[PDB]
């Protein structure tokens, strides 16, 4: 159904060394398709996804310019900020930026955002209406004002509504056969020799995609949602991820406890 | 399609 | 501001000692991005490693995924070392088979 194309470009300060390492990256539904990297022998926006080879040099050039340009912006900028934060030129920094548009299966845009951050803690962000500015601290509100003068909200909002959605609609078409693959998870349970004369049922799900997955331990319809310490959905390797669940259960009575795995790619939810 | 940024932060 | 590296370790498949597997070492929530990683085994630094997906979630936290070509043997023991400004000395995670 609906989708999202977002870009997460960062800048790391290397004052003494010689130049910040502005690195950009691009995603279409949690899937990375382009990355730049201002430290490479040849700065080039190389295709990650396979479906991005079919574009051409016409499009691979038009990009690397936008790249080096923002490089300047992340440079020029980053510096003004040690002035704002009255920090002596030496402490490494990180100016970050993220943007994109979320489109409903229907076709029209649903929401778009832009956000900057300087060393983690938020610095400023456009609001939902695409017109307001949520500046973080005093040194950041300085910017909120200045941007309302040139009309940051009408410039960026412009890119959001049309173009971001426009190109998005292009990407999906080009990589349709790949992007919409929904790999279903594989069932697996486990019990361990824990010293308390207890057992540990481990509900193992592997090779799945997308990652948004629901997973719990049961006991008669009602779900043992409290004792099941589970993991943080982590990247297996090839492309399909994995997740696991835990419930400490003494012998004999074990057979009663169960696991359940919910995921967008199953015809009937799984009960193990 | 990365967009350009004029307005210096 | 600094956020400390959460280290997770795990194989790419259920391990049955012998079969050439891919031992990962996923990181999360470290910041600033400058982090040192080291793949180990009984203390001999594993020479061949990886560095993929160096990106960041909305929480402005940079991460990575490193993996070597480990091979399970009930007698040996693997691990993953990592240095990151937001801590006095490097933390070490020896891998537990069924995790
Ligand atoms: C996904 O790939 C294409 C593009 O999204 C889908 O094709 C639809 O759109 C075409 C125009 O771009 C129309 O001309 C086609 O009639 C229409 N359907 C087909 C079968 O091409 C296509 O359906 C999708 N493919 C899959 C496997 O879902
Ligand atoms: C650091 O500079 C002054 C001290 O000269 C301090 O009071 C201030 O809080 C800091 N800078 C800003 C912009 O507040």
Image (tube, helix red, strand yellow):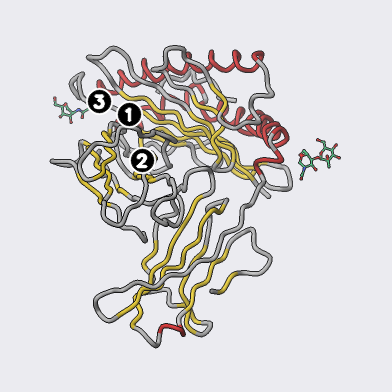
For mark 1, does the 10 Å Cα neighbourhood hold few (<14), some (14 to 19), or many (20 or more) residues? many
> Residue sitting at 43 percent across and 45 percent down?
C20
Discs 3 and 2 carry the same chain letter: no
Residue at (43% x, 42% y) in the render = C58
Q: Residue at x 33, y 44 (%)?
A: C29
Q: Residue at x 27, y 47 (%)?
A: C79
Q: Chain of mark 1?
A: A
Against C14, residue A21 (above or below) is above
Q: Are marks 1 and 3 in contact (CB under 8 Å)?
A: yes
Residue highlighted by disc 1: A94
Q: What residue did someone put label 3 on? A: A92
- Secondary element under disc 1, as helix, strand or loop, is strand
Whether the residue carrying mark 1 lies under 8 Å from ligand 2 is answered with no
Pointer 2 indicates a residue of which chain? C
User: Do the residues under discs 1 and 2 have CB atoms within 8 angstroms?
Assistant: no
User: Is C10 displayed left or right of A271 in the figure?
Assistant: left
- Quadrant of the image occupied by residue A146: top left
Badge 1 and badge 2 in a common chain: no
Q: Disc 3: which chain?
A: A
Q: Position of residue A89 (x, y in %)?
A: 21, 18
Tell me which image quadrant ligand 2 sits in.
top left
Alpha carbon distance from label 3 to label 2: 16 Å
Q: CA distance from mark 1 to mark 3?
A: 7 Å
Position in image of residue A2 (x %, y %): 66, 47
Q: Which residue is mark 2?
A: C61
- Foreground residue among A119 and A228: A228
């Amino acid at each position: 159904g609906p989708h999202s194309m977002r870009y997460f470009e960062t800048a790391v300060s290397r004052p003494g060394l010689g130049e910040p390492r502005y690195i950009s990256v691009g995603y279409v539904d949690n899937k990375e398709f382009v990355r730049f990297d201002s430290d490479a022998e040849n700065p080039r926006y190389e295709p990650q996804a396979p479906w991005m080879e079919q574009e051409g040099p016409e499009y691979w050039e038009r990009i690397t310019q936008i790249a080096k340009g923002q490089e300047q912006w992340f440079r020029v900028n980053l510096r003004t900020l040690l002035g704002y934060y009255n920090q002596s030129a030496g402490g490494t920094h990180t100016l970050q930026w993220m943007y994109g548009c979320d489109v409903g299966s229907d076709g029209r845009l649903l929401r778009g955002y832009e956000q900057f951050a300087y060393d983690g803690c938020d610095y400023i962000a456009l609001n939902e209406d695409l017109k307001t500015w949520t500046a973080a601290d005093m040194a950041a509100q300085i910017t909120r004002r200045k941007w309302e003068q040139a009309g940051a909200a009408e410039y960026y909002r412009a890119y959001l509504e049309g173009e971001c959605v426009e190109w998005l609609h292009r990407y999906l078409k080009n990589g349709n056969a790949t992007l919409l693959r929904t790999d279903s998870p594989k069932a697996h349970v486990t019990h361990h020799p824990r010293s308390k004369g207890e057992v540990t049922l481990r509900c193992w799900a592997l090779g799945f995609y997308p990652a948004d997955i629901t997973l719990t331990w049961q006991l008669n319809g009602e779900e043992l949602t409290q004792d099941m310490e589970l993991v943080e959905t982590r990247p297996a390797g090839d492309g399909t991820f994995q997740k696991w669940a835990s419930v400490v259960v003494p012998l004999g009575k074990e057979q009663n406890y169960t696991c359940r795995v919910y995921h967008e790619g199953l015809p009937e939810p799984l009960t193990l | 399609q990365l967009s350009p940024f004029p307005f210096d932060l | 501001i600094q956020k400390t590296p959460q280290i997770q370790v795990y194989s790419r498949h259920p391990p049955e000692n012998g079969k050439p597997n891919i031992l990962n070492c996923y990181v999360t929530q470290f910041h600033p991005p400058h982090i040192e990683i080291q793949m180990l085994k009984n203390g001999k630094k594993i020479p061949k490693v990886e560095m993929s997906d160096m990106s960041f979630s909305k929480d402005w936290s940079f991460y990575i995924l490193a993996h070597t070509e480990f091979t399970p043997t009930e007698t040996d023991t693997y691990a993953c070392r990592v240095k990151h400004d937001s801590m006095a000395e490097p933390k070490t995670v020896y891998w537990d088979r069924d995790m």
